[PDB]
Amino acid sequence: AKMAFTLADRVTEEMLADKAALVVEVVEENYHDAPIVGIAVVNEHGRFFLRPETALADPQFVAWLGDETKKKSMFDSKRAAVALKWKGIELCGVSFDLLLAAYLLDPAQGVDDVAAAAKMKQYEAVRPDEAVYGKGAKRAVPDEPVLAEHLVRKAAAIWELERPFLDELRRNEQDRLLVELEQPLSSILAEMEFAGVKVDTKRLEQMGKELAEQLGTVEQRIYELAGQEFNINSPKQLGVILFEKLQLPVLKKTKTGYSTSADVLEKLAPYHEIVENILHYRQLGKLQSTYIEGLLKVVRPDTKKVHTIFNQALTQTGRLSSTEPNLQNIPIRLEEGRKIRQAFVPSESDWLIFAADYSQIELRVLAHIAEDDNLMEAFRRDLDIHTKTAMDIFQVSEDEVTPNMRRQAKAVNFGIVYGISDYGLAQNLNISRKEAAEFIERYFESFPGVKRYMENIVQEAKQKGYVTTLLHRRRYLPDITSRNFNVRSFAERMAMNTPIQGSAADIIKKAMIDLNARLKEERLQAHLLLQVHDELILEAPKEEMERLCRLVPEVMEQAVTLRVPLKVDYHYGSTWYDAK
DNA sequence: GCATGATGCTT
DNA sequence: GAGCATCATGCA
Ligand SMILES: OC[C@H]1O[C@@](CO)(O[C@H]2O[C@H](CO)[C@@H](O)[C@H](O)[C@H]2O)[C@@H](O)[C@@H]1O
Ligand SMILES: OC[C@H]1O[C@@](CO)(O[C@H]2O[C@H](CO)[C@@H](O)[C@H](O)[C@H]2O)[C@@H](O)[C@@H]1O
Ligand SMILES: OC[C@H]1O[C@@](CO)(O[C@H]2O[C@H](CO)[C@@H](O)[C@H](O)[C@H]2O)[C@@H](O)[C@@H]1O
Ligand SMILES: [Mg+2]
């Protein structure tokens, strides 16, 4: 039942047709400077397997890869593009990416290989990658015969599935979303990842040493106050010290045992001096283990750069994620952790970091979609939205809004931006679910348009089976009809929140595409380095800062036209820390 | 070795 | 709330 193909010893003309399904296999999860283990090509002339050493050395094949007029259909083209970039080879003409197509059709399926995408259309003549390569320590590239058949079968699947996937995308009015947004963005992400971000390793190592000293000191104080040594990082061992030896009250429990989360510890601080030290230990340990040690582990020793990998096909909101290292959660709230950003520097001499972020894009999107008169007017006046929200829900003038009032209004807005439940709000504000509900009710009284939107979108999700974003991204919500309160409730919150978060995701993605086109037209050397949800980070010659101050915000603010203005703040400096 | 729980960082 | 990590702990 095997599939016929040619195990080529050399590249031939028929292998270079103007349309083909192409597989450039990179098995390592992190594809940066990784091996390409095999190549498969499927076109009108047949199916072929090529050894990388020969194909990638062949002038004709390389030229074919870089020829934009020679169209290729692939799965996870970014992976191939980046691996090739590390080899000095350009990949152009990718007209269809099955990974992104499957992702847009249904992001909940978690499609991570050709077999999974193929199963969506009842095509199963291809094996899952895990079945071929294995997992974990058992992972390995199989003998050529097995490897070759697998790559050819993946190419064959891509060749066959392009049409049915494009047809459904078209039916969903998502064809442009794929071809004009996600695929072009994939190439931009490839460039960003390959460029990488330069790291001041000496700085990190310095901080690391200072942290180690501070950790040792606090660690000893903890054992001193506890009257014995124990594993502080062990909730079980810590729980015994706090709730048994010291008799602190148990305010919250977890499946396993006593909760020792920061939230719980804060409340116990008044009872014993050991508590504040545990909190301080947790903070220092977080910075040391996750950030300092974590970053140093993935920095390339030769260039001192980190090359993250953006997962463009994971979230059901349409936002991008980042891994190895995750550069979307570097500390900023507290000054101590914020200092870590001083370690991210420009990659060239006399260059600077330029960062631009949307100001409240989620709430502005909500104002637009819900057509709430009060919210739209607030943004048209460029009001401090948290202060404004406080004025309305607490019924007071601007000068009557106290700091605590603004903080709680901000939390209410935070809940709307991330679609948290009333229990979530209650927990965040440390108040009763009942009081949190009253805040929500007060908010809806002040923003009736938002209330109407929330009611209507849940109804629409139920009727159609999914909700959509500004650029037609879709999220199916089968749990919307569940008779299990918690399950149904979460689905309703996602129905309300996905159009907001998802539309904001669509906007910044388009902004990235528009920005790169503008940078090219303007002949600027400036280039994108990172995307952190509502923020874009670039680096460029110091001589280009003034031009970027006008160009970047303009492009970002004009990415789309909403019923309210889009506002972008920006700053630049010698390090990411200073770009604020 | 590897799965899962508790924890905490960002937006 | 999600996605990404950590370390500890159990088992396997
Ligand atoms: O290449 C990224 C792309 O690959 C998938 C699998 O198809 O994820 C793999 O690579 C990621 C980055 O190294 C890992 O986080 C993930 O664990 C691994 O399976 C897609 O999800 C992703 O879009
Ligand atoms: O020195 C390591 C040894 O100490 C214990 C406590 O007896 O844990 C300490 O060190 C760990 C690694 O530095 C921390 O994770 C932990 O929080 C700290 O108390 C033992 O578990 C370990 O064998
Ligand atoms: O009381 C109506 C109000 O309830 C919500 C949940 O807060 O939805 C419930 O009632 C709907 C009937 O109109 C059902 O479709 C839905 O499944 C049920 O949870 C709100 O959406 C609605 O405004
Ligand atoms: Mg912002």
Image (tube, coloured by chain):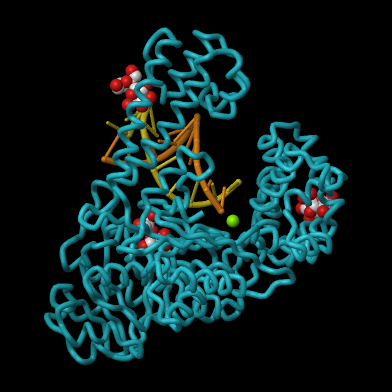
Chain colours: A cyan, B orange, C yellow
On the question of residue A191 being in view, the answer is yes
Identified at 42% across, 67% down, the residue is A528
Q: Is residue A325 left or right of residue A66?
A: right
Q: Residue A236 location in percent, x, y?
A: 45, 20
Q: Is residue A110 left or right of residue A478?
A: left
Q: Residue A322 location in percent, x, y?
A: 43, 55
Identified at 26% across, 54% down, the residue is A304
Identified at 56% across, 27% down, the residue is A254
Residue nearest the viewer, comparing A454 with A48: A454
Q: Is residue A520 left or right of residue A414?
A: left
Above or below, comparing residue A322 to residue A487 in the picture: below
Above or below, comparing residue A101 to residue A459 in the picture: below
Q: Residue A261 location in percent, x, y?
A: 54, 28
Residue nearest the viewer, comparing A466 with A275: A275
Question: For residue A169, what is the image quadrant?
Answer: bottom right
Residue nearest the viewer, comparing A478 with A35: A35
Task: Count how many numbered circles sit on residues in the image.
Answer: 0
Looking at the image, in which quadrant does ligand 2 appear? Answer: top left
Residue nearest the viewer, comparing A492 with A355: A355
- Which quarter of the rendering shows the N terminus of chain A? bottom left
Question: For residue A149, what is the image quadrant?
Answer: bottom left
Q: Is residue A460 left or right of residue A525?
A: right
